[PDB]
DNA sequence: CCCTGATTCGC
DNA sequence: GCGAATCAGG
């Protein structure tokens, strides 16, 4: 998949909750923990 | 051997 | 903008 606005919203919610990158990756599907960390960085979190 | 985030740069 | 493959550890 791709970083749709929906998926980014989910990432932000879960990260702001303190879930780890691998946990978020598993919840989302379609991305690795690497992709999640990279997106967290580009979002400025 | 399970796990954590951080970074570079080809794509 | 994206994320594999490191980096740097717990």
Image (tube, coloured by chain):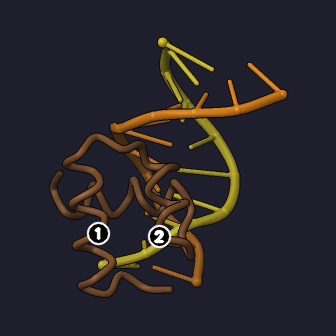
Chain colours: A brown, B orange, C yellow
Q: Are marks 1 and 2 in contact (CB under 8 Å)?
A: yes
Q: Position of residue A28 (x, y in %)?
A: 47, 70
Q: Can you say whether A28 is above or below C1 in the image?
A: above
Q: Can you say whether A32 is above or below C1 in the image?
A: above
Residue at far left of view:
A44
Image quadrant of residue A32? bottom right
Q: Which residue is mark 1?
A: A10
Left or right: where does residue A34 sit relative to residue A36? Answer: right
> Regarding mark 2 in the picture, which secondary structure is present there?
helix
**Label annotation for residue A33:** none
Kindly identify the residue that appears in the image at 36 percent across and 44 percent down.
A19
Q: Nearer the viewer, residue B4 or A16?
A: A16
Q: Nearer the viewer, residue C4 or A22?
A: A22
Q: Position of residue A45 (x, y in %)?
A: 17, 51
Left or right: where does residue C8 sit relative to residue B5? Answer: right
Circle 2 Cα neighbour tier, 10 Å, few/some/many (<14 / 14–19 / ≥20): some
Q: Can you say whether A8 is above or below C7 in the image?
A: below
Write down the chain letter for disc 2.
A
Q: Which residue is mark 2?
A: A28
Q: Position of residue A42 (x, y in %)?
A: 24, 63
Circle 1 Cα neighbour tier, 10 Å, few/some/many (<14 / 14–19 / ≥20): some
Q: Can you say whether C6 is above or below C5 in the image?
A: above
Number of marks in picture: 2
> Regarding mark 1 in the picture, which secondary structure is present there?
helix
Kindly identify the residue that appears in the image at 52 percent across and 54 percent down.
A33
Q: CA distance from mark 1 to mark 2?
A: 8 Å
Q: Position of residue A36 (x, y in %)?
A: 42, 59
Left or right: where does residue A35 sit relative to residue A19? Answer: right
Image quadrant of residue B7? top left
Could you tell which of marks 1 and 2 lies nearer the N-terminus? 1
User: Is there one chain holding both mark 1 and mark 2?
Assistant: yes
């Amino acid at each position: 998949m791709s970083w749709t606005d929906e998926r980014v919203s989910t990432l932000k919610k879960l990260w702001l909750d303190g879930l780890s990158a691998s946990q978020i990756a598993k919840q989302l599907g379609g991305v690795t923990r690497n992709a999640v960390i990279g997106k967290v960085h580009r979002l400025g979190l």
